[PDB]
Each structure stands twice: as C-alpha cells, then as structure tokens.
Image 1 (spheres, rainbow over the protein chains, first blue to last red):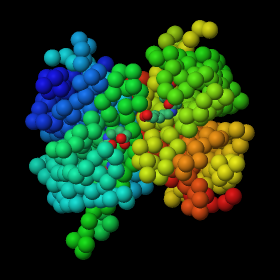
Image 2: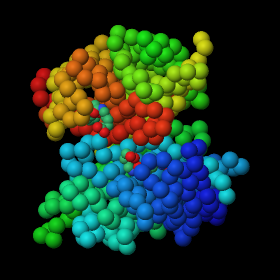
Image 3: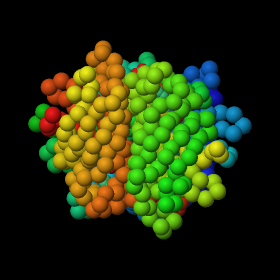
Image 4: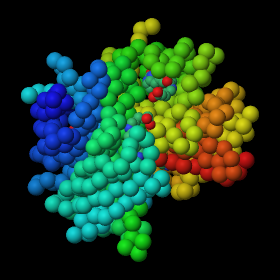
Length: 124
Length: 127
Length: 125
Length: 125
Ligand SMILES: O=C(O)CCCCCNC(=O)CCCC[C@H]1[C@H]2NC(=O)N[C@H]2C[S@@]1=O
Ligand SMILES: O=C(O)CCCCCNC(=O)CCCC[C@H]1[C@H]2NC(=O)N[C@H]2C[S@@]1=O
Ligand SMILES: O=C(O)CCCCCNC(=O)CCCC[C@H]1[C@H]2NC(=O)N[C@H]2C[S@@]1=O
Ligand SMILES: O=C(O)CCCCCNC(=O)CCCC[C@H]1[C@H]2NC(=O)N[C@H]2C[S@@]1=O
C-alpha cells in the first residue's frame, strides 16, 4: 500500500544523516542508519514499526525506530529512538523527534538523555 | 552475557503497563507490550535494540524500543518509542523517556507528539 | 552587551508565531507571545531567563521562557516552556525545543505533555 | 485562591533539588532554585507562569518555569525550563518534564539539549 511504498527507500537529513529502510509485513521497519555526527561511523542496524493502515484522509503515517550505536567498528554505549510521521508528495518527508540515551552511572543518570528533532527527505 | 540475561523477562511500571522481551542476537529486542492506558487493548508487537557489550564498570545498558499501536483488533494511528537504560540487581529497572506521535494533518503536526517518563521494574522469580 | 542587544526585539517562526522580548537586568526576559495555532487568541505574558555572560568561543547564548495560556481573552489551562539558544549575525536565530503541559485529571496525566521544536528569526521592526 | 496558596512554598525532589516560589499576581511564579546535581552552586533565579484560574473538575494546574544557570557563584552557560502541573491535596505534588539547553557551537548544536522528569513534594508552606 501507500505507507509501504512511501516509507520504503533511502532518506537523508540536512546534515547528511542517512538511512535505508524497508517498510512491510503489516508494520515492520528494518534497515540501516548512518549518522554524519557524533560518536558513530558507518552503518548501524535499525528496527522499528509503522502504522500499516493509516488514516488516508490527509493525515501522516505514524512510525518510529531504534538504533543501538554499536556496530562492527564502534560502540558508543547509547541508543536513539525516533518518533514521527511519514508525509507523502513530491518532497516526501519523515518528520521526527528523537531521544538519545547513554548508559550511565546512577549519579549521571539525570543527564543521560538528549532530545532533538530530525526531518528527512526521500532520496531514492 | 549480563545484558541479555538482565533485560530478558517481564517488566511492569506503576500503572500496570507491562512488557515481555527477549534480548539476544548481539543487540536485538523482540517482544510484546500491553498498555494499561490510552487507546490500546491487549498486546502489541515491540521491536528494539540494546547495547550488547555495555560499559564494564557500573554504568547502565542503553536500549530503546518502538510500538506501533495497531494489533489484530485495534488501530490508534500512532507509535511510541522508549529510550532508556537497563540496570540490574534484585530491583532491576528500565528507566525511560518516551515519545508518542500520532498521524496528523500538516496543520496539526505541531501537536502530534506526546512525551513522558516510564520506569519499569522486572518481575522477580520470587513473584 | 551583545546578548542583551541581540535577544531584544521581535521574533517570528515559520508559522507566524511571534514574540516581542526585552533582555536585561543580568538575565531577565520579559515580553509577550502570540500563537498562530492552537487554543490561543491575542498576546500572552512571557517571562524567562538568559545567560547574561555567555561563552565567547563561538557558542550560542542559552535561554528559556514560559507562557501560561491565560489572558483576558482565553484560558487554555495550559502552559508552554521553550528551552534553546540565541545565535547572532545577519541570520540571527533562536533555536528551541518546547514542552506544553495541560491541566489534567490524574487519569489523563500520562498524556498531559506535548513536545516540539521552534526556530525563530528576528523581525524588523 | 487554592492555586496560589497551593503552589507558594518550598518544594523538593528525591535528589534534594529544591525551589522556593511565590505564586500570585494572576499568574506569576518568582523565587529561587537550587540544584543538588550538575554544574551548579547555591541559589539561582526562577521565573515562570501558572494558570491562575484552573479547571475545577479535578484537573491539575498547568505551570512552567525557567532557570538560567548563572548566579554570583557560577556560570554553566545553560538554561533549564520545567513544564508541568500542580496537584493539590495532602500529597501535593508538582509533576514536570524539563529541557536543559547549553550554549554550543553550531557543530555541537545537535547535542545541546537534555531532557528529563522531576516530581517535587511540598516541604514547607
Ligand atoms: O557524542 C558524544 O561524543 C557525547 C554525547 C553522547 C552521545 C553518544 N552517542 C553518539 O554520539 C552516537 C551517535 C548519535 C547521533 C545522533 C544524531 N545523528 C542523527 O542522524 N540524528 C541525531 C540523533 S542521534 O542520536
Ligand atoms: O487518549 C487519546 O485517545 C488521545 C491521545 C492520542 C494517542 C493515541 N495512542 C494511544 O492512546 C495508544 C496508547 C499509548 C499508551 C502510552 C502509555 N502507556 C504506556 O505503557 N506508556 C505510556 C506511553 S505509550 O505511548
Ligand atoms: O490535543 C488536543 O486536542 C489538546 C491540545 C492541548 C493544548 C492546549 N493549549 C493550547 O492550545 C495553547 C496554545 C499552544 C500553542 C503551541 C504552539 N504555538 C507556538 O507558537 N509554538 C507551539 C508551542 S505552543 O505550546
Ligand atoms: O556533561 C555535563 O556535565 C552536563 C551537560 C551540561 C549541563 C550544564 N548545566 C548544569 O549542569 C546546570 C545544572 C543542571 C541541573 C539539572 C538537574 N537538577 C535539577 O534540579 N533538575 C535537573 C534538571 S536541571 O537542568
């Protein structure tokens, strides 16, 4: 359907953070994420979920995903989740907010979690 | 290792929101989630990731997961993500913040995303 | 100083949400805020704080402010705070994230708080 | 009214973070905040707003405040805002979420803002 065909593909933000994702199986997001910033290099596994039967009446399609920042080259002892929605059109977008939590001692737990926003445009 | 054995099991918060998760395969989380609140009934697929080789000296283990609020009988047109960390011990905890986004019109996108906090405690074998 | 002169003035985001602010007295923000969206009409009181001695290493100036959405026209039983930083130069910006909490019963407290992001540019005049 | 009497006083969280606030003037919060954690020493100025005519259906009272982490002792080049609600009664609480932004260069702006929660209990009228 349109949610599957819309989300599936490659997405990039203004900083060149890029992900490749497949949307299907009635709600699964799978793919890989590459950050252009922070303690990260090369690709990280992405897993998430999306609404596979969205309100078709001008609303976006809700979705989210997770990346743990460990791969074969690096481990940043952190994970990020993005929560947002897919909007179609010529300039299709995934508009999100994100939360990045680092593993901490209990003393530093109050400062464990960064928050931000990320808008992705579809590249292929 | 300890992150896999610590995280895997059954977890619930002060409201009775509960999940069952398995941590393995070098950083995968899979399970089911049940909310006691909101436009939700019964169980929903959970998928996420965790740090499979956490810092060695008393830090928490970073993890996150996602639930889209559609299952076999309900669809709330929304998805939540939880980002947080695991800590072990007898009162093991997963301490998180969450973001819940609804599909909206572009005019209403400014009000699409709720935010909150959720501390889960692991059900012990002694239960 | 630079931070007082830079923050002081009229600011608007892409949606036409607008505020007018004065920065002074070693850290005080005072002004009015007008929202183009939501359960809001006319101008609301804004109060906040800023770092009146910011780093001079190229960093922005931290700041934050609060609006309770009650005025003489409307009461939306809610309040928003913005947390962010000011950056000067010809494309001066205040880049923020915000938290909007509504008064709720305990049963609805779990869904009391919205989050978003807001970038403001300086208006003349 | 009960919002003013309710919110005015001394509050603390589980970590010992404490603020002393006066609520009045049809929606003003004024006082000082002391953190027990982080790059903070002694008392900082607090300014905020609250809903001075809240719903009477059992709902909490929306509120928000800001602290810039500059005082006569220290400057941490950052500001925090708390958005939340006051719930009255015999276990009077202020339940909030917060956003802490540091001034940063543009290279570091992506990591400028921390997020958390804070529940406060009233320790003194
Ligand atoms: O990064 C530091 O050196 C200190 C802050 C602690 C964070 C540790 N983890 C990381 O740096 C992993 C990479 C995070 C990248 C973030 C950025 N890139 C994107 O594509 N979007 C944003 C959000 S994601 O969390
Ligand atoms: O309640 C309404 O109908 C208005 C809010 C619109 C959101 C629609 N989505 C839902 O209600 C799905 C359920 C969300 C449950 C939330 C709550 N339960 C938990 O276990 N933790 C929190 C976060 S989760 O997002
Ligand atoms: O989801 C629902 O049906 C209830 C939403 C509850 C929010 C009630 N409060 C309001 O509508 C007051 C106005 C909020 C305006 C928000 C928007 N305008 C801006 O300039 N920036 C954003 C953040 S501000 O909180
Ligand atoms: O890496 C680090 O050292 C932390 C990031 C830089 C933050 C600098 N600012 C500060 O440390 C000022 C103090 C923040 C205190 C926070 C804590 N205390 C409370 O009462 N509640 C929380 C939120 S508040 O922002």
